[PDB]
Amino acid sequence: MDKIRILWVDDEIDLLKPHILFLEKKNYEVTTSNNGLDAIALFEEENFDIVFLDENMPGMSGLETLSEMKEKKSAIPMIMITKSEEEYIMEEAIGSKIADYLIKPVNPNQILLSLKKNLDDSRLITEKTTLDYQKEFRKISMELAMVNSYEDWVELYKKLLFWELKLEDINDQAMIEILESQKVEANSQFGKYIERNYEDWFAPKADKPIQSHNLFKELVVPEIKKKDKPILFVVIDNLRYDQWKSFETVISNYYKLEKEVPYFSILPTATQYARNAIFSGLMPLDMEKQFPQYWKNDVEDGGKNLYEAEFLSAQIKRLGLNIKEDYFKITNYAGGKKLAENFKALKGNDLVTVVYNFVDMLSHAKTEMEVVKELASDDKAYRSLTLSWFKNSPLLEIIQQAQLLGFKLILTTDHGTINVKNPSKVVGDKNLNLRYKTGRSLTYEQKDVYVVKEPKTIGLPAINMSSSFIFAKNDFFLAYVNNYNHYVSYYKNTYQHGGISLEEMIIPFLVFNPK
Amino acid sequence: MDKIRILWVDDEIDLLKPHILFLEKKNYEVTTSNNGLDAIALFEEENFDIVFLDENMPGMSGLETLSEMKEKKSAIPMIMITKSEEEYIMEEAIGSKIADYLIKPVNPNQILLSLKKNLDDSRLITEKTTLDYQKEFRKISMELAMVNSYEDWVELYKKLLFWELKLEDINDQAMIEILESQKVEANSQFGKYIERNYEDWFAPKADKPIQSHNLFKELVVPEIKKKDKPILFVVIDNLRYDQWKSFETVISNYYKLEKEVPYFSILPTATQYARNAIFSGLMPLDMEKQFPQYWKNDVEDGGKNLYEAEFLSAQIKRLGLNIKEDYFKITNYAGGKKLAENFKALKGNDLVTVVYNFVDMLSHAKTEMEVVKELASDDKAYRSLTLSWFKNSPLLEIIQQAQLLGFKLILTTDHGTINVKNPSKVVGNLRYKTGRSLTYEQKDVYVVKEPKTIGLPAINMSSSFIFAKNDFFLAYVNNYNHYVSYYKNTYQHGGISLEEMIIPFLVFNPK
Ligand code: BEF
Ligand code: BEF
Ligand code: BEF
Ligand code: BEF
Ligand SMILES: [Ca+2]
Ligand SMILES: [Ca+2]
Ligand SMILES: [Ca+2]
Ligand SMILES: [Ca+2]
Ligand SMILES: [Ca+2]
Ligand SMILES: [Ca+2]
Ligand SMILES: [Ca+2]
């Protein structure tokens, strides 16, 4: 049975005979029925690809018929073809998960379009994506080669992201491998770019992107100073650009995007440095000088982000803002639910700052790491898991609450993560699992890392003059020499951060108005 | 509140003045542009809610414009409004992720429809679903009351599942609690039904649903005997009917459903008993008798499902089948990947049996790992995480491989699981217990003082089984408060509920 089977329910089948003949010439098989009751029985006994429903029928309405049919077989698309132009009927139909609604008199080609849209869209998107990428990939490879500035890197990354999400679900493995290879080459070139240019960004009056320590003052404070709406400022820990893309469509049910500014995490691309920098408004070295009671170096025991509220309150004072402002750090579901359920207590704030931790992608427990790997083995899976997370997170409940109170939403992150593949040995560390190491006696493969023997020049502390930082490039992960083989097999294909990649370093900043 | 902003690109803006006036009366703000390139600039510098594109324009075509706009801001819906009736234009537009395509001359109300459908559908679905359930729930309560057979229980469960998935994205808490109360009432009645009928199902010539120990012979062997295609037989441990429902539409990309048979797990609704029964073709008591070298009772140490291949091979021999047949048990990602990558080795089998434990692992991890607790905090979340898992699982890769080799797919499970809520004291797994001198609340459990009557082993005449009903968990009187705190809202199985006991058996042909 090659031909598409349409069931068409309408009390006036006579009048539709032109459309039926037209569809039959175009190789559709139409079975007609002149009342809902019989249509339902037919629909139970046979396998239609699609149903067309009149609305105004003397027995059961189209929508009553649809409701019965959907209960039996909810995956079959249902199209309403009706003379009714009334808005309330439109709304009922839409609310009933109609796949389309065509107003009589209908152009027969409008029905054909609808059939293509509702039955062939998946195939046509795959084909079109596939052809378009076949024609595009060479131009992407060459654009990559010509990339010369941080802004070109942003534009190229945006291109890769766009194609990544489109090629997710195609089947051609050749095209998928071509893209994988472009991503590797992009990260190789980006690594060299950062290696060559990062230090110069700290010179006075340098051309540089917005970075962690600039973020609040350059992008958040203007929104505060508009004095238009209270602000919910959310930092999702460790979110990549593609993770944002994965739930863009969900958040749009509540919030309309007004502004999107890609910015660059500082190095290391890690919470202790970049996230504290967001809230302090200072590079780590300056946090060590100006706030020694809050700054902790890697060597010190305990939480590395305990004092973000204190940092943020001090920053807000230095910038001469007089606002009602609170900070929340959610590290678990329970915490998240409590804040969602109690969010209305903050109706009077100018600013609510929420740090919202994602899932731990790097467990030291094998069974937990097995769970993560089954859920997030590759980038597509990671996105899928992220989308599931966001739809069902207390974070989204917090956002809905904020929307109902007319808050503006600022959504951003401290840095992303990258799926690591290639091990690189490091000795001496005396530390966890990140794509940076710091210490006074490090040995390493210098080709694999960006090496900074003078940390203070990029705003990082140094215990003494032997302190160095190394930052992994590409998809390297830094592996300890002891138990090397087991380490490599464990941490291969995990989401790590701390180093240089488009994924880790170029991250979204987003401003939205409540819908 | 704030007006919807439309950007409309057409080289003949003059001729669209009626449509624009109509939309403006209906509170749309229209910005017009007569060529794609200027439209692109506008589209970069402003946040439009939606774009209308003509196709035939001098300069950039609609489709060229669309391509540029989607790259810049891919989440903004775009509608083509064009004189072009060409099929290839239709297909290109569709393939380019157009949200709609309206053929000129367009009824202005057709545009309005499109705007409502593409911008308001979430809200309209919520409202409509909510009112549909408000009008239906009384009829559901009545169907519940009229349930007198196992097949009626299957039909009613199907109805609850349908409404559960529909109500997952509504807001009204009253309506949500009404449904929760129908589920509780269904499980209370189902519990009594099972209590009253279960022993009698083992009487000769009893009218009874297919059960674990019948499953292979009654439902798998007829498929083997058609001798048409090899069979991939997948047992996903611990799959609830609603989890099947959550990924039905994914499977359908590869496999067409031929037959669905809901069946009943035996008691306890637990792997050691019900899963072994599937593979052995025997009740646990008979497994203890006929295969004491494989059967393990609860007290014995070590894995309780180590010998399923051997049980299955023996069953196949008893039923007089001569087939090439292998069994695989996937306990991790690595194992799953290996099997997907090397599946073609099994092209020559009549039967491949794959047990996949991951969903079982999730259900316990919801309590233990903070990752999964954040991801699977309620039933909606659990389904969502299951669907994300399935779409990106090695299991689905195995299924795709099987499809490419023309295998028939049989998909089933051993039992489901239920979110436990209410504690029930016992002193001597939390939905069944076995032992000789047990205290319990008889109202909360199904009590079997003679295990042999329901095909279960018995240490002594004193030894009995109790099976939790409803959403009870069996809690020890010592450390009761800590017990209750810890186990409330965890996934458990082993007892009686629709979730635990009525489970899918599914047969599909490769597409
Ligand atoms: F009588 Be109808 F809804 F065209
Ligand atoms: F900007 Be494009 F469609 F090459
Ligand atoms: F010039 Be068109 F495609 F209406
Ligand atoms: F496979 Be189980 F822990 F009943
Ligand atoms: Ca009619
Ligand atoms: Ca972080
Ligand atoms: Ca030095
Ligand atoms: Ca034109
Ligand atoms: Ca271009
Ligand atoms: Ca099981
Ligand atoms: Ca279990």
Image (tube, coloured by chain):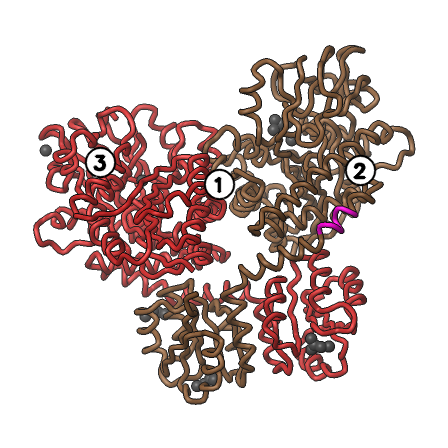
Chain colours: A red, B brown
Q: Which residue is mark 1?
A: A375
User: Taking B61 as reference, is B190 left or right?
Assistant: right
**CA distance separating discs 2 and 3:** 63 Å
* Magenta stretch prevailing secondary structure: helix
User: Of the residues under marks 1 and 3, which one precedes in the sequence?
Assistant: 1
Outermost residue, right direction?
B205
Is A141 a magenta residue? no
Magenta region: which residues? B137-142
Q: Residue B263, image x and y in percent?
A: 76, 39
Asked if the beta carbon under badge 2 is closer than 8 A to the nearest atom of ligand 10, the reply is no
Q: Quadrant of residue B280?
A: top right
For the residue labelled by badge 2, is the local secondary structure a helix, a strand or a loop?
loop
Q: Quadrant of ligand 5?
A: bottom right
Label 3 is found on which chain of the structure? A
> What element does badge 1 sit on?
helix
For the residues marked 2 and 1, what is the alpha-carbon distance in whole angstroms? 34 Å
Within 8 Å of ligand 11, the CB of disc 1? no
The disc placed on residue B261 is none
Q: Quadrant of the C terminus of chain A?
A: bottom left
The amino acid at mark 1 is Leu
Query: Residue B85, can we see it?
Result: no
* Relative height, residue A13 to residue B488 (above, below): below
Q: Are marks 2 and 1 on the same chain?
A: no
B435 w.r.t. A10: above or below: above
Quarter of the picture holding the N terminus of chain A: bottom right
Residue highlighted by disc 2: B210
Chain where mark 2 sits: B
Residue type, label 2:
Ile
Instruction: State the image coordinates of residue B28 (x, y, percent, origin top left).
Output: 45, 74
- Quarter of the image for residue B149 reads top right
